[PDB]
Amino acid sequence: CPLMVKVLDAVRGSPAINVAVHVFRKAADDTWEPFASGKTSESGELHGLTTEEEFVEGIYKVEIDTKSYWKALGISPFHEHAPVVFTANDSGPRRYTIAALLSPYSYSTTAVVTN
Amino acid sequence: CPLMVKVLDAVRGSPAINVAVHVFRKAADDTWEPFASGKTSESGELHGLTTEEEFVEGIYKVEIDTKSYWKALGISPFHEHAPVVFTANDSGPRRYTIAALLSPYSYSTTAVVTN
Amino acid sequence: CPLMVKVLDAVRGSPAINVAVHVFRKAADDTWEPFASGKTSESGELHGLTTEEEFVEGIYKVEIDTKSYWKALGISPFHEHAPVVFTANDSGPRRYTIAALLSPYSYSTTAVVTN
Amino acid sequence: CPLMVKVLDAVRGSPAINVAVHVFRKAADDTWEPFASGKTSESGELHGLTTEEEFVEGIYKVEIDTKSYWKALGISPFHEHAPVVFTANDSGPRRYTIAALLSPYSYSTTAVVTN
Ligand code: NA
Ligand code: NA
């Protein structure tokens, strides 16, 4: 698996558990088409979204459902969700980790791309 | 000025100048409709996107064109752009500052909402 | 105003008001000597810490008292404080803004340095 | 091992490899005393700093040597280092991960405390 998502909670100092994540790929007609989805584990990680066979070059969007996460914790959030948009390029062997750090009114995202 | 955008460059420790920003608002048909756009100034700020009259309740997307910013500096970055999605003016008018802090493979965004 | 400090609260999406800040400068004996201090205003900013005359070359530490800020809000945070350590004015005078974005278990700090 | 350090590089989109990390504990005389140290691995992680026996309650400082990291990559940095200061409390079983995300003029740190 070439694409992993990891989410942390900056208020509790914990992995962000049970966060829904939806991945889309841009189609030929320029629309976002569903590609993969899941919920983060107890470690805040989401593994097994795709395979090397299916994860071809293209433009992808990883949407982290931040609003539902904060509401389930009884906390008042700002954003609807956190979308992370990027091109996947076959510049040799690569693994992509989309990491995100969440606060109710702020978030950061980092791409960790390794060989 | 109920909606302002501020962008900083984390590599240089400076305002991110001439960054293009496109704002959209979700329409009744659920599509993203163009709402306003502009570019950041020498201070990294973008003022005058809208007015209290035009900035009605709704779901908005502020898209910061991070890829074009890094490419104009001769750098190949990871993300296509940084979209920031939120509901605005649902409890009456507020002033919103959407701030972003950019690095080639990472960004943070914060909302500062004042009454 | 060659040294300014700005602090935001990532939980509320607001300026962090009344945050204590202590600045130190490394002395010849390698100890941290008090240099200036103050508290952030209603805008989350702290102005007037020093003057161009007093702000000589040196190694400085800007300590943001994050624990006292969260405790005054009735929250038990992780960090004791957020120290920001850097050399200043080594290539002539510059204006420095030390910005910090706070959450109970996490913070970010950015330096904006202008000539 | 109850204390782990993880560092990412926001410019390259990679683990921050070979970063020196120095941990100190506050002594009875209020001075910072060396406690443990090491360099991050190829995964950007530093394991085996201490043991449950030695990691008693107290005030600790984890110093990440950011300036030397950026200089070894041929990149111009702002901060001397990134110090992370906190109390370790035996509120039941706990593991502490000090995570940091580095850019030349900005960094973030998050504490992930799990049971
Ligand atoms: Na406006
Ligand atoms: Na000043």
Image (cartoon, coloured by chain):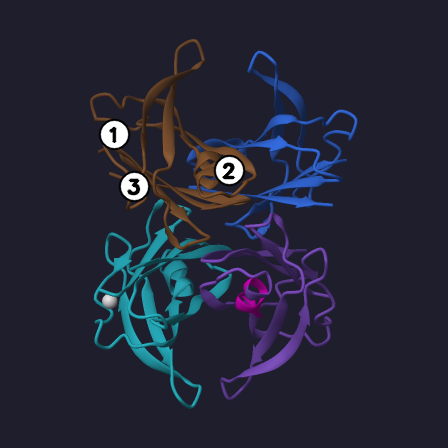
Chain colours: A blue, B brown, C cyan, D purple
Q: What element carries label 3?
A: strand
Residue type (three-letter) at the residue carrying disc 2: Trp
**Chain designation of label 1:** B
Residue D77 on image: x %, y %: 48, 62
Which chain letter goes with mark 3?
B
* Amino acid at dot 1: Pro
Q: What is the spatial separation of the Cα atoms under label 2 and label 3, in whole angstroms?
A: 29 Å
Q: Dividing the image into 4 quarters, which one contains the C terminus of chain C?
A: bottom left
- Relative side of D43 to D58, left or right: right
**Which secondary structure lies at badge 1?**
loop
Horizontal arrangement in the rendering, residue B65 relative to residue C22 (left or right): right
| Residue reaching furthest to the top | B29
Q: Name the residue under label 1.
A: B93
In this rendering, the answer to whether C108 lies above or below B108 is: below
* Residue receiving disc 2: A70
Out of B112 and A23, give the one closest to the viewer: A23
Above or below, D61 against B77 in this view is: below
Q: Distance between the residues labelled 2 and 1?
A: 23 Å
Q: Is residue D17 visible?
A: yes
Residue at mark 3 to residue at mark 1: CA–CA distance: 21 Å
Which residue reaches farthest bottom?
Answer: C29
Looking at the rendered structure, whether the residues under marks 2 and 1 are on a common chain is answered as no
In the displayed structure, would residue C91 be above or below residue A30?
below
Q: Nearer the viewer, mark 2 or mark 1?
A: 1
Q: Which of marks 3 and 1 is nearer the N terminus?
A: 3
Q: Report the magenta stretch's main SS.
A: helix
Q: Label 3, on which residue? A: B45
Q: In the image, residue C13 lies at what x, y percent?
A: 36, 44
Find the magenta span and give its range.
Answer: D63-70
